[PDB]
Length: 223
Ligand SMILES: [Ca+2]
Image (tube, rainbow, N blue to C red; front, side):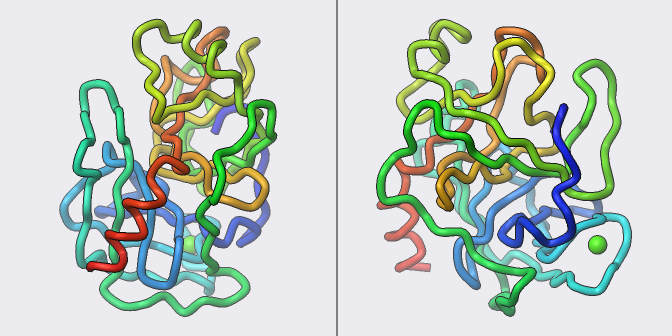
């Protein structure tokens, strides 16, 4: 997250870190057994880390649970990042408590102009590289579809939305991929892509989670 703030330990209790020997993407806990992340975060050998604040210090509220199964969307296209969504099943259920909690899936799509909370352990520099240890947060508004298509001509599908600041300076970035965009208390987005981070006229692009709730529900009913 570039231009954000330190969230405060365990104040984003649905945020997970995906670990393959190191943090490499975020995700969102949607019930005791399942995590939503980006398909472009797929790796074999994922351990889900819940209850994290500092990813490099065991502070006492973590749960580390191996994935048993990962399920990339059936129509994910890694060239265009259309349908950039994945489900990860945990080998055992998380113990839900004040610091490890699920985020609700949406019923309706979020409105343009809504301010959402984006969070992660990704890079905090627009130019250059600095990865934080503690969870960072950013409040960013959903942009109109037409502003998002103007920013990325021929690349935005109806399964993507933009959010952020066209003047630059505030954005998600590498290493935040897969993490949450929460708007009015629902998971509405997944950190997906963008041209650089926090660059003028190049806002972040997010997977539009409300288009996938029927897939998520039938998949979790079946696995
Ligand atoms: Ca920790």
